[PDB]
Length: 48
Length: 48
Image 1 (cartoon, helix red, strand yellow):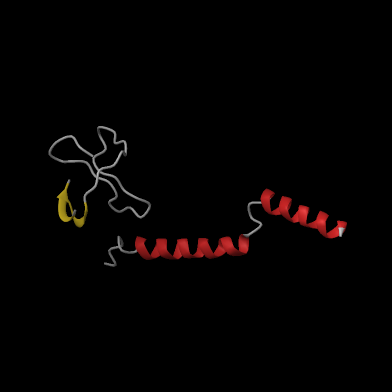
Image 2: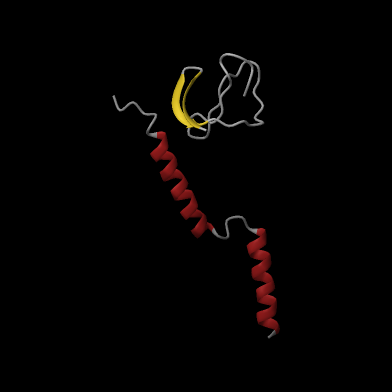
């Protein structure tokens, strides 16, 4: 019980301290931001 | 109201609303992250 309770305290500290901890979900927001930003940016492109 | 506007040579359709955005005297119209019209200044009189 102390091993679980102490390990959950370490999960709280790790997730609150590291900005890249959720990088697998941040890649979903980042991919959609780059995709939608390219999708809008290309409306300003002349295409010839 | 949603209206067709032509301001500072920028023609488009949109709702014309007031904002608190600070424009410098020499900066006539604004752009957003996509380089598209977000806020403009009145080409006739002094207004944002």
